[PDB]
Amino acid sequence: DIQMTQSPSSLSASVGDRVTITCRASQSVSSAVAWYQQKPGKAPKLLIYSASSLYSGVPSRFSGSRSGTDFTLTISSLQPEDFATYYCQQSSSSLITFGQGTKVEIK
Amino acid sequence: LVYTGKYREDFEIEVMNYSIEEFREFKTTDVESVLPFRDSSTPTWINITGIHRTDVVQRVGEFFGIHPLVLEDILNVHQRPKVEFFENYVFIVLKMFTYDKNLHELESEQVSLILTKNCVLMFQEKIGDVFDPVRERIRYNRGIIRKKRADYLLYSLIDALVDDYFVLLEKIDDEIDVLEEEVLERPEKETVQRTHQLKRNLVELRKTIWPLREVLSSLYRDVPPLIEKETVPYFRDVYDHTIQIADTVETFRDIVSGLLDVYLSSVSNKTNEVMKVLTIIATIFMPLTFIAGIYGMNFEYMPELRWKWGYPVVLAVMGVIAVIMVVYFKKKKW
Amino acid sequence: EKRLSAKKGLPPGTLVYTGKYREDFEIEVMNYSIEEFREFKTTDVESVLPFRDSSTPTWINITGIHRTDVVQRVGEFFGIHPLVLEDILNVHQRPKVEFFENYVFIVLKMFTYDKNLHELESEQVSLILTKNCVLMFQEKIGDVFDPVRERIRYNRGIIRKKRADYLLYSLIDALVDDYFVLLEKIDDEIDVLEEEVLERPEKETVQRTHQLKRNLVELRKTIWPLREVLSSLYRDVPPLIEKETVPYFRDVYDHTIQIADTVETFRDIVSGLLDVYLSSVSNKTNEVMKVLTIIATIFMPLTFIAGIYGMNFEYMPELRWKWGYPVVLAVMGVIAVIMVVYFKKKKW
Amino acid sequence: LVYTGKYREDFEIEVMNYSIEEFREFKTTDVESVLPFRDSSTPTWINITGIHRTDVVQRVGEFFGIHPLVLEDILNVHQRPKVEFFENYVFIVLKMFTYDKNLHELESEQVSLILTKNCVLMFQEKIGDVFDPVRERIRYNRGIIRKKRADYLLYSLIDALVDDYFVLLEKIDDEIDVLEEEVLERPEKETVQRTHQLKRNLVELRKTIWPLREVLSSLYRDVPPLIEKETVPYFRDVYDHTIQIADTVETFRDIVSGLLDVYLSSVSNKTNEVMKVLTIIATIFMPLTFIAGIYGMNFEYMPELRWKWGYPVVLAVMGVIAVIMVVYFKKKKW
Amino acid sequence: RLSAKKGLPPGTLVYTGKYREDFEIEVMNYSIEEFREFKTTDVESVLPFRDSSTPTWINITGIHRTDVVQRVGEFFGIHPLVLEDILNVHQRPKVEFFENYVFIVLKMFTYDKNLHELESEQVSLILTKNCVLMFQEKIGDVFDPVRERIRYNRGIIRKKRADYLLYSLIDALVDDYFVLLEKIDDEIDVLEEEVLERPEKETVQRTHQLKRNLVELRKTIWPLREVLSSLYRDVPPLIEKETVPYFRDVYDHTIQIADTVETFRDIVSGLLDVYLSSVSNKTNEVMKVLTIIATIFMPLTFIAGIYGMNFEYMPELRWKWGYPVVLAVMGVIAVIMVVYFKKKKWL
Amino acid sequence: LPPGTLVYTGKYREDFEIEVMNYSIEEFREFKTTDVESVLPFRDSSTPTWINITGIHRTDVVQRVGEFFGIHPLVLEDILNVHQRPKVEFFENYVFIVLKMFTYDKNLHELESEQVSLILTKNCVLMFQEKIGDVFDPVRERIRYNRGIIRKKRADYLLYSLIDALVDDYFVLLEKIDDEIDVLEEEVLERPEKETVQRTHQLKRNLVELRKTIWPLREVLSSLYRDVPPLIEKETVPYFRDVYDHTIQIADTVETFRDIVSGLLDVYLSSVSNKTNEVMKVLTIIATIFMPLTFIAGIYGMNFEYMPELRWKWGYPVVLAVMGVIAVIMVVYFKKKKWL
Amino acid sequence: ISEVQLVESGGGLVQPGGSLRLSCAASGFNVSYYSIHWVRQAPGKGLEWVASISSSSGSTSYADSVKGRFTISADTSKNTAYLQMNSLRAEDTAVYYCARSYWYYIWSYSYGNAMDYWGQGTLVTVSS
Ligand SMILES: [Mg+2]
Ligand SMILES: [Mg+2]
Ligand SMILES: [Mg+2]
């Protein structure tokens, strides 16, 4: 079972800032990593797949990249609606796992 | 009949004689215990982890009725994967791989399979392999392995080997990602060494994966009586998996070759830059060395006393000529 | 025997879009005849399924194949073998042609070239020719088949008076025309890069040159299978294609021949450009090493003799040669100017 | 309608109606009146010059019923030559190249030819063409120019054009020989620029000539609608001339390509010789200066003293080590 | 040589090859129910098989004896020009159709890994009625799998006619082409490693030899496509319609071979440029070392000669530890220059 | 000039002869004359005849010959024009063939070309040459000595035999050029020089000239075979096809030679780069040895008043010893680096 | 025709050690061409993947946290995927989402799937 370690868990920033969330895998996950955002009381929404490809309809401020077993999600310029919890996901195996989450708070 | 490899350290012979009703295992080092298993109706799996101990392999060779030439084939390590068909058994040569993430070093281990009626034989040079899932499936009655014949055991072994190749490809994929990132921006001599080593690794991988595709194709396409007709789709699946692996290997080769080409493209600029540096440093110091040497000559009529205080004027002209050379080098962007 | 492929870490029967474009989806149909035509755009596939059993030729164009459900449904309703659908969804492929007793399946490539970033991007387009339908499969909005659309819309040419075979010919002809315009773009890019390579030889220049080299190699590996496809089209005529419309396919084959020859000439030109770059950089290095060696030649012997007169043997004729030192400087100047004259003789 | 031409200095109209008995020459500077007006009795060759006065183009197009599409096509400079066939007339567009040794580039102008029954209407952009031999052939009644019909006029014009291309390629051959002699004797930094200019000129002529070759290919063997069958061997001859010109262009491109490679080899040899001079002088003069600085150190107690002309002994040992270094270079071929 | 039989009348049977030591005739007459292997030396033994009602494969190995070739051609009614093309080893691969037979010329390659040498042997096939006539230059074939499939009914070989036998032979020859391509790719890889790692003169000589081998191979392969395309697309009366798809498959294999050889040619073309780049990299490492040494030691010797001039007005009378302070200046300059070189990542 | 002009553009006017060989299955005759009227009455003949009017510099004789045979003035212009691409023309009465003959010089490294023309009318073969000496001697020997099957055929076989002899001469030329390419590749692989580049450039120019002449010959033979004229008998097309195969083989050989000569220059560049690397290695070794030692000699050659220099650990020998130690350390370092 | 929708049904309060079944109605798409996933999010915790079904092939995958305790299945005719939960524990209390994913391509040997459309989610409470 591949473990995704997502840090930080309690990021805080103001609107217009730059958010970086980094995510690490316990072993090799060949670029099969996706990101989701979940506002409280709702369902998760897909943002990035293949660790770089931007999902259709997702705002262009979201970005992703892969450095080996290290993955990062960036909100280049925060918005009032960009405050939620973001998760990792590996799908290189039939058993797919999530990260523990990262809440971006209003500063 | 000599072991041509390097691993001549450890020895032990495992046995897994299994059937639907029950299974029996024992890890023993004495030759005579693993002999009478050819008469067992139930499928049997013998694993000889020592090849340098040529006595045991010769003994089982003349006990199982397998030609001495293929015995030499087991005892030979530097040999690409191959398959041979004989009336009594089928001979298959395969390779395992271990890749070190830190050291970037890829080493290979040969495994040889001799499949006879209701019995399969391995031959390894070292302790450690990837056939463990097959062992677990034989133990806890997980799949359909225990309810079938020895050819299915051969299929499971080859399937495990191809799965290990998939894992190795994952490791190489991470390495290629990081290496491409490093070469594209901020390259270094260590990065070039890593690129060369990874290219060599991929060359070895291609050279050992193409014969594997050939072996699996010859396995399922024309089926010798040793392989049942029901197990053909399984070997066909393994053939498809080998196709996947070879395609990934080719793509990685192309990426690494492009990485090398882009780096070697810019060598002449490096030559020109080193020339510029050396020329600048040599030109602004040789005339100064000359004038210092002339004024350090041991003649007796040198006006080296007073004469506008002596050393101030020579230091001034050295500075003036140095800054003039610097200005001259400012032109043409040196 | 043809068979669907088993892929590790993937359920046995699933078909996967092997691509990068997932932005948009569209289905466009033009049902045309001698008298009247009709065209509409839709998302529902049931709106376009019944055209399979139709009399007048129709051109069903499906943009966006990331919708594997639509591809599977169309292939099932039209009776397309699953391996052909798996080939449709695979874009890491070379152009190909496959003949079946009920349909013919063709793979082509489309190219958009950008002056900025010097990027050569490929889009795979698939054609299935059936009893009276040509199935168009694409990945994203934007193609080169506007001329065929216009001819259908205003009864130009002879396309309205023919069958689906002429429609297939027209689409392939338009794609080859796009190949020609791409080759012209490559002319422009080679001209710009050759202008820059002679006087500004840098690392980004050779990066661009090697990018062009790889682009041309890809263009060759694309054009050769295209030429084979057209050769098999006109010189192995299947039952789906009439005895007519074969001269047209021969014309398209000739056009492919011209394109291949132009690609070879491009490869030769770019190799010449790289040689020019290396020559220029080598000439600059020659100039700098020439100035270095002139300085060294003028000064190292002179520093040597200054060191000779800078040592102390206590019994040397150090003086009384008209003070000697002026004679030493005279020898310095004489050998320096002789070396200067020699360098002028060598035109350095 | 609109044109991309740049020169508007000169406008002139030439009329030339000729037959066996006599010919008419007026040379009116205005439109005046065109003699044939579709007379279909005598061969008429009217020359117009200039494109700024577009009204003449529309007038002649409307009078003789020329389709407006080709009329729009004529008023261009960047279009490649092409041929179109119509029942009423045949439209052929060509180009003329002029070359000078002083500046080393080519000026291009577009020429159109329209052939109608006993009427050959043409187009022009500059004065002073190569059709003076054709005009002299008209005037002095030599050959078979004054024999039959008007298509032979078009053949004569095309023959004059291909003769001009032949002499232009001869001039290119002369300059290629000159540049070959220069490269094989005197290399320079500007020589590569000159050769690049020549190569771009060659690629431009390669771009332009092949459409003319295909136009002449379509003129012959296509069964033209209205052309006398007695003039087809002449079209074959001019087609062969175009074929020879194309082959000569390809060979010229090959030679110019090889010139770059010989220049690159010369540059590398230059680097090598400069390097050898630097290395030889450094080797011959660095140890000598080291020894001189050794005997010049200020150590109070040194064994050095006058020992049978010690200063000549040290100078002699310096000289002999210089000699051995020199002979080492000589035997090493430096 | 290429000017053999220069001044000779057409149809003159002259052998233009380097093999004059071998000769044997092997006949493999097979039917649906039985076969009969037969090896002989006499020409007259194989002549009765001209009218046998079963598929026959007469393999004449060793054509330095023009008498055998002429006798066989006369009995089978082959035109003398076809015979003189049979004996002409340096003929281009081709296919020619006549009224009663089909004439084919192919080349099969032998490769040597120890000495990077490419050898070619010309093999000619004549397809007359239910008979395939085969001519070679030396012992050693590539059709042993075909022989074995005839011996033991592994396939449909004995159920079909002579055209299927011709198919089998062409297919085996194309299989050798695939094997040879594998070997050449292995040598490509080893030479690429040699070029990138350690450039030498032996390396450039091997690269030139490999380039020559690839140009010969390419010149040979391209006519093979034309031969196969002529074989299956246009039907002669001698080839049944049921064998056409097989010839189409072999044509596809030739397509693959041509594409692979073009890739190999591209790599070999880039090899020498890579070699020059690598040698430039090595000499630039030497350049960097020389530049570093000069950069360190020219300024220090300059300031060691400036203190050591014979001017008698400097404050050298133990100003503030003159020798120690100048040595400290030496060390400071050397350290800062080494730091600069480390920053630029040369050292 | 008008198309009917009969100017001759060539460098050869020294000699002029006319050679006629009329042969038949039972009758054989041959004679050389210097008069056109002597050889003129052969057009209305029922036996194959070979008229070889060599030495094309007097245009009057060929004008008269064309007038007798009805030869069109345009092909008179083309046959009197030396700078003509190899060509084939078909006419209802005759077929016109323009070919070339090549001479190569080993010592001068120069390639020379001679233009030969052929006109086949009914049962007559008219040959036109620039000078004397050609490659058709075996044809004459076969006709004279009763060999082959030439004497029992029509003029089509004679045309084929002449073209076949010309192609065989081309084979000989390509063999000589192969020998030259072999010696050049040996000379560039073993002992490169400055003149190597010029020699390779000359060989490249010769090869491009060869290709420029050869490819039209292949086209001419292809048209001769594929589009059979009514003049050439149906039975003689296989011979023309054999000559066509010879032409395509020659073209392939020319292409191979071009590739090899293209690679020669890169081989030369690799050699010179290796030389440059060796000489830089020598320079770096010397400089590395002798800059630190000069620096030390300068340090201990100063003029500072306060120096621990009188007698410190024997004084003078110790610095020489430490410089020798530095020198040997650097020498063994270079040996380990394999630079030396 | 219509937008892609996922609706869950069956969330309820079940005694520990008991059983309940959750339904997932699929609208706007055919359940055969896609893979249906169940995702579990405990109150105050993050997302946890629990199950997966490939209806066309019938392939299933289960997390080790529920392996041998859950069962996932689909009805192609009903366009509905199921999750049979029995032998429930107190830790199974969560909101259970239903999601749809597609397979995408990275290399020849590597594949990945991303979840596009999620259901509202139903809450299951194991207590008392
Ligand atoms: Mg002193
Ligand atoms: Mg000194
Ligand atoms: Mg012959």
Image: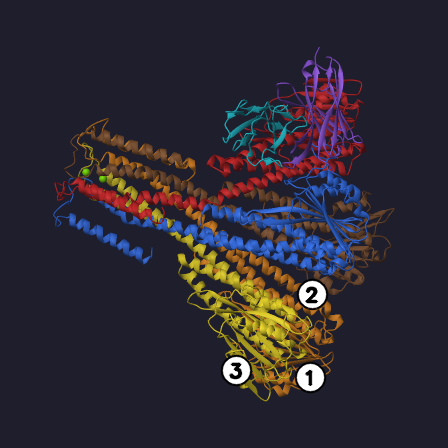
Chain colours: A cyan, B red, C blue, D yellow, E brown, F orange, G purple
Which numbered dot is residue F43?
A: 1
Q: Pointer 1 indicates a residue of which chain? A: F
- Say if disc 2 is inside 8 Å of ligand 3: yes
Residue A1 position, x and y percent, is: 64, 23
Location of mark 2 (residue): F242
How many neighbours does mark 2 have within 10 angstroms: few (below 14), some (14-19), or many (20 or more)? Answer: some
Q: Residues within 10 Å of mark 1 (few under 14, many from 20)?
A: some
B272 on left or right of D78: left
Mark nearest the camera among 1 and 3 is 3
Quarter of the rendered structure image containing ligand 1? top left
Q: Are marks 1 and 2 on the same chain?
A: yes
The structure residue drawn at horizontal position 65% and vertical position 55%, both measured from the top left corner, is: C176
Disc 2 is placed on an element classified as helix
- Could you tell me which chain the residue with mark 2 belongs to? F
Mark 3: which amino acid?
Glu
Q: Which residue is mark 3?
A: D136
Chain of the residue displaying label 3: D
Q: CA distance from mark 2 to mark 3?
A: 50 Å
